[PDB]
Length: 216
Ligand SMILES: [Cl-]
Image (cartoon, rainbow, N blue to C red; front, side, top):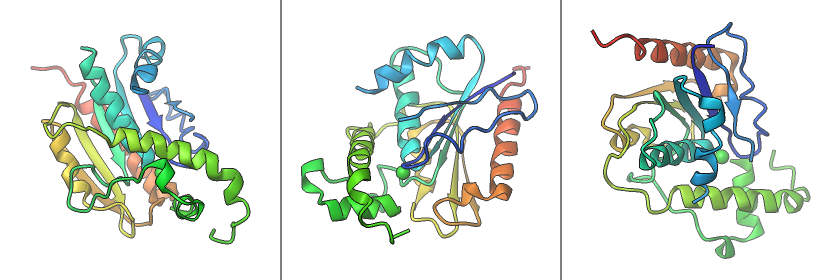
C-alpha cells in the first residue's frame, strides 16, 4: 500500500465504520479505538515506518487528529501529509462553546451529547461513564490550543448541510497550508451516506497522490 490513513472515530462508533480497506491497494487504514497525545505519537511509530500518512477524523476525532498532528510537530516528527477534519466546530471561532467540566455536567446534559434515538433514556446510565470520559478527551483536545498556525500540512474540512458543526471555514487558521471546505448533503453523519463516503474517499486518494508528486 502506498499511503497510510489514520482514522479517528466519533463518539459511539466503535472504530468500525472506518474499516475502509481494499481500494484496491492504496490505503492501509488503521483506526484509533477509544498529555494523552504522547501515548498516540509513539504508538503510530511502528505502523508509520517511513511511509507517507494522512489523518481523518469525525466530530470528536477531528480534535484528536488535530492535536496528534500538532503533537507530532512538537517532537520534530513529520506532520501528516494531509489533515482531513469532519463535522467539528473549530476551537477558535465565533460559534465555538467550551465544553463544561465533568463535575458541572448532569446526567441529563450527558444524555444530550449521546444523541449528538431519544427513546433510549434508561440506557444512558450505562453509557454515561463512556460518554463522560470521551468528553474528557475532547475537553482536553480543545484546551490551551495555540492561537498561531503551528501546522503546515494541507487541510480539508468536510461538513453536512444540516450539520450541527458550524464555521469549519475557520479551521484554516490552524495551518499555513492550503485550506479547503466541502459541504455535502446530510446531517452530522452525512459521511455514512455511501455516496458521501465515496466522494470523501476518492478526494483523500487524489489529495495524497497530488501532494506526492516530485518537486520539479
Ligand atoms: Cl463525537
